[PDB]
Amino acid sequence: SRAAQLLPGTWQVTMTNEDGQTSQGQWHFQPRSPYTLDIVAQGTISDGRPITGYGKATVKTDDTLHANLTYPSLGNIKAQGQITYDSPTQFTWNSTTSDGKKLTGTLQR
Ligand SMILES: CC1=N/C(=C\c2cc(F)c(O)c(F)c2)C(=O)N1C
């Protein structure tokens, strides 16, 4: 998977959520196997809430992975979504939180 092959390391993450907030931060990827990478998440939401999270991305196809994250700094809510390749330096994030809220964003280098 080319997508999985590009992901190792640090990406700048920006998101918007359903409540009209934005977040800025990073996702750090660590490959674990040919199909899997671990994630650690750090950032801030526009209302001041700090983001501390972690999770795992699993290869689905050449350009798509499914990722589950959990966020101890956000009352342990979770997020499940797809990481899709856009370019060697950009991925897109489309997910739903465990509160049923839509949460999308981008990964950039
Ligand atoms: C920037 C950023 N926002 C993240 C998560 C996140 C952002 C939000 F705005 C949420 O409402 C929420 F539930 C999770 C994340 O992991 N990073 C790195």
Image (spheres, helix red, strand yellow):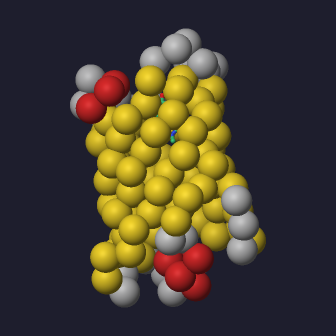
Q: Position of residue 68 (x, y in %)?
A: 34, 53
Q: Can residue 92 be seen at all in this image of the molecule? A: no
Question: In the rendered image, which quarter contains the C terminus?
Answer: bottom right
Name the foreground residue: 2 vs 53.
53
Classify 56 as above or below 70: below
Classify 60 as above or below 94: below
Q: Quadrant of residue 59?
A: bottom left
Q: Can residue 51 be seen at all in this image of the molecule? A: yes
Q: Position of residue 63 (x, y in %)?
A: 58, 77
Q: Name which residue lies at 61% across and 34% down.
A: 24
Q: Quadrant of residue 77?
A: top left
Q: Name which residue lies at 32% across and 53% down.
A: 55
Classify 55 as above or below 78: below
Q: Name which residue lies at 59% across and 66% down.
A: 84
Classify 41 as above or below 91: above
Name the foreground residue: 24 vs 80.
24
